[PDB]
Image: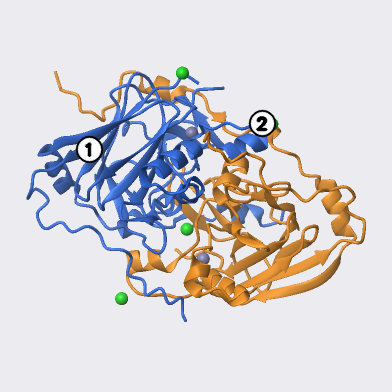
Chain colours: A blue, B orange
C-alpha cells in the first residue's frame, strides 16, 4: 500500500443519485385510487413455474405470499413493446440495492421511464439487518440453468430464467429462444439478500415473508408482467416451494384525475453525432 | 389497543433479522483459473499494440484469446468504463450481473468477467491489480465495480433535463459503431452494463444507496487481464474523471501483449456454456 493509503480510504462517500434529485410520485393519489379499486383478475403461479399477467396503466398489481414462504422473480415489459423492459441496474443506481414503497421500477435505455411504483410493502419494516440484508432485491440476476451447468454440471429446467422464458414464449407466441433473449435481470420479490460486509459477496438468507405478506404496485404504463416461483423456495437452504398469487385491481373511473402515463425519455439520442 | 397496519413490524422481527447469511455462490464452487500459467506467460510476453483513450471518449481494441490487455492510469486519476464482446459474435458480451453474483460487488486478481446468457463463459481473467491493497474501506467502498451501469444521457435528461453527449453510454456507442460499421442505434443496443475500472464505490451501510468517492488510482496504476476468448474491448474515459465531485479528466492507456510461443501449454480457451437450452421443452 502507498504511504497515503489511509487518507485515500478515508475520503467520504457521495451518493451518486441523491433522493432529492428524483421525481416524486404522487403516492397519495395512487393510494386514494387504490382504496376505490375493485379486483379484476388473478393469476396463481405454481411452485417452480412462471406465469405472465397483463396490467393496464393506472391499475394495480399485488404479489402475495400464500401457503408458505416463497420468493418470486419478477420481469416487466411494456405490453405493447416487449423490447422496453425492466432495468434493474438503473433502478439500483437510483434507489439502492433493494426497493420498497415510493420507489419505481425503471425501464431500460433508451426508454428509461417508470414502469411501476411500489405503493405498499408489508415487509417495509425490515430495513437493513445486522448483516446488510434487505428484501426485494435489484442486485441478483435470477437463478439460471447456465450457471447451474457451470457450477454443478447437469441440466435443470425449472430455474427462474427458464420459467420466465417459457411463460413469456407461451403468452406472446414468440419462439422460445427469442423469448429467452428478452428475459432480464429480475426484481427478487420477498428475497432477503445483500453483500457481505467483509468480502462483498452476494448472500441470501431465509426470507422473512409469511403467508399474507404482499408487495403492491401501481402500473405506470400498460405492462406484461412475468413472475417465477423460484425453486429456491424461501432461500433458507444452507427447497420447500409454494405458489405465489398475483391479483389485479382497477380504480374507479376519475380517481386518477388528469394523471398521465409517464413518457419515454426525451434525450435526443444523437450521442453527439 | 392501537391497531396494526399491514407494514408494521411483527413481534419476531429481530429473530428474522438474526437469521444468518449464506453466500449464494461460494468461491470453492467456482472453476479455478490457472493464474500461474497466465502470469508465467505474461512475463514472457511482448507488446503488440496500444490504444490511447482520450478523456470523455471511447475507443475499441481487439485482443486474441491467449493475449493480455492492460488498462493503465496516465497523466492523472481517471476512471474507465469497460465493455467486452466476443470479437466474432458481438451478441456475446460482458454480463456484469452474473460476474457480481459469482465474485462480488467489485473484482480483482483471479476473478473473471463472464459473458451473458446463454454463452456464460469466462471472457477475461484479471491477472494483476495494482490497487489490490485497497480492499474495502470504512464506508464499504472498493475499486473496480460491477454494480453500476454506466453514466448515460437518458438518466441525465431525466434528472437534469438537457442533452449531454459524452456520458460513457454514448462514448461506448460511438466507439462500437465506428469500429464495427454498425449503425449507431444498432451499436447502442449492444452496449452493456460496465466494469467500472478504477472507480471507488459501494452501497451505503445505512440506506443501501450507490455511492462513489474520489478514486485512489494514480498515474502508474493498472489493471491487467488475460483474454480467454477473442475480444472486442470498448473503453470509455468517463466524464466524471476520478469521480471525486461532491470534472478534471484524463486519458486512459490500453496496451496489448502477446505471450511467447508455447507459453500457454495445454490451456484451453473456454467453450460456451453446456446447458442443453431446452428449458424443459
Ligand atoms: Cl451432465
Ligand atoms: Cl416442494
Ligand atoms: Cl450508474
Ligand atoms: Cl432541454
Ligand atoms: Zn430462482
Ligand atoms: Zn461514465
Q: Is residue B24 left or right of residue B230?
A: left
* Residue B87 x, y percent position in the rendering: 68, 63
Q: Nearer the viewer, residue A95 or A255?
A: A255
Q: Residue at x 25, y 52 (%)?
A: A220
Secondary structure category for the residue under label 1: strand
Q: Residue at x 36, y 53 (%)?
A: A106
Which quadrant of the figure has residue A217? top left
Q: Nearer the viewer, residue B76 or A127?
A: A127
Q: Is residue B217 left or right of residue B257?
A: left
* Chain hosting mark 1: A
Q: Is B226 located above or below residue B232 in the figure?
A: above
Q: Is residue A135 left or right of residue A20?
A: right
Secondary structure category for the residue under label 2: helix
Q: Is A1 located above or below residue A244 in the figure?
A: below
Q: Residue furthest left?
A: A254
Q: Is A219 located above or below residue B164 in the figure?
A: above
**Quadrant that contains the N terminus of chain B:** top left
The residue wearing badge 2 is: A152
- Residue neighbourhood size for the residue with mark 2, other residues' Cα within 10 Å, grouped as few (<14), some (14–19), many (≥20): few
- Residue neighbourhood size for the residue with mark 1, other residues' Cα within 10 Å, grouped as few (<14), some (14–19), many (≥20): many
Residue B94 is marked as none
Residue A248 is marked as 1
Mark 2 or 1 closer to N-term?
2
The total number of labels drawn is 2
* Residue B128 x, y percent position in the rendering: 75, 54
Which quadrant of the figure has residue A166? top left
Q: Is B262 located above or below residue B28 in the figure?
A: below
Q: Nearer the viewer, residue B250 or B180?
A: B180
Q: Nearer the viewer, residue B78 or A249?
A: A249
Amino acid at each position: 500500500a502507498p504511504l497515503d493509503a489511509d487518507a485515500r480510504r478515508a475520503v467520504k462517500p457521495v451518493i451518486c443519485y441523491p433522493n432529492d434529485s428524483l421525481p416524486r410520485p404522487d403516492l397519495a393519489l395512487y393510494r386514494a385510487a387504490r382504496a376505490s379499486a375493485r379486483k379484476t383478475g388473478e393469476v396463481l403461479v405454481p411452485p417452480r413455474e412462471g406465469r405472465c399477467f397483463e396490467v393496464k396503466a393506472g391499475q394495480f398489481f399485488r404479489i402475495s405470499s400464500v401457503e408458505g414462504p416463497q420468493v418470486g422473480d419478477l420481469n416487466l415489459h411494456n405490453l405493447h413493446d416487449l423490447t422496453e423492459r425492466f432495468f434493474s441496474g438503473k433502478t439500483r443506481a437510483l434507489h439502492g440495492t433493494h426497493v420498497t414503497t415510493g420507489e419505481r421500477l425503471w425501464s431500460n435505455l433508451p426508454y428509461l421511464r417508470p414502469m411501476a411504483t411500489i405503493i405498499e410493502d408489508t415487509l417495509g419494516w425490515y430495513g437493513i439487518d445486522q448483516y446488510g440484508g434487505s428484501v426485494h432485491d435489484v442486485i441478483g440476476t435470477r437463478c439460471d440453468p447456465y450457471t447451474g451447468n457451470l457450477l454443478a454440471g447437469g441440466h435443470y429446467h425449472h430455474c427462474c430464467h427458464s420459467n420466465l422464458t417459457r411463460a413469456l414464449a407461451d403468452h406472446t407466441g414468440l419462439p422460445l429462444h427469442e423469448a429467452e433473449m428478452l428475459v432480464h435481470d429480475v426484481l427478487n420479490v420477498f428475497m432477503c439478500t445483500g453483500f457481505t460486509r467483509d468480502t462483498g459477496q452476494y448472500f441470501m438468507k431465509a426470507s422473512p415473508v409469511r403467508p399474507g405478506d404482499y408487495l403492491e404496485f401501481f402500473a405506470e404504463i400498460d405492462l406484461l408482467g412475468n413472475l417465477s416461483a423460484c425453486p429456491g423456495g424461501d432461500c433458507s437452504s444452507e427447497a420447500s416451494c409454494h405458489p405465489l398469487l398475483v391479483e389485479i385491481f382497477a380504480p374507479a373511473e376519475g380517481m386518477l384525475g388528469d394523471w398521465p402515463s409517464p413518457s419515454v425519455n426525451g434525450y435526443d439520442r444523437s450521442h453527439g453525432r
